[PDB]
Image 1 (tube, each protein chain N blue to C red):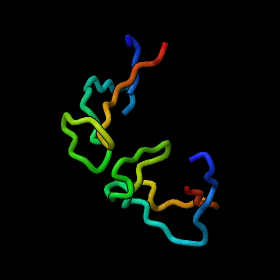
Image 2: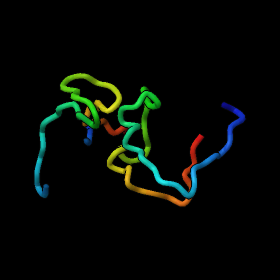
Image 3: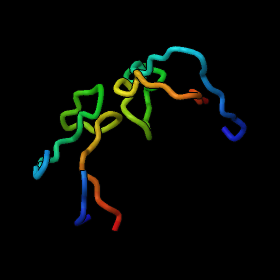
Image 4: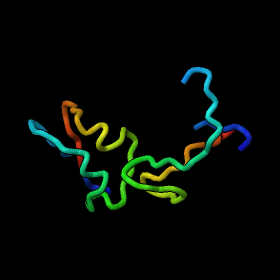
Length: 49
Length: 42
C-alpha cells in the first residue's frame, strides 16, 4: 500500500458497467460518473492499481 | 445545518433517498443508496 505504482491499460476495449454489481466491487465508490452511464467512454491512459 | 443543497423555476421540496444506481433502496442507505440533501459546512 506504501510501495505501489501507476500501472495502466492500453490499446484495448473496455466494459465498465459490470462494476455496478460484480464481486470485484462488492464494496465500491467513485469521484467520477456512474459505472454503466460512463462505460462507453475512453482516455489516453487507463491508469489502474 | 440550516443551509442545505441537493426544470426552470421548479422547487422540488421532496427528500426521498436516491436509488442512485443498481439497487431498490426505498428507505435503505448504502452503496448506490444515497440521501439526496446535504448541509453546507458554514
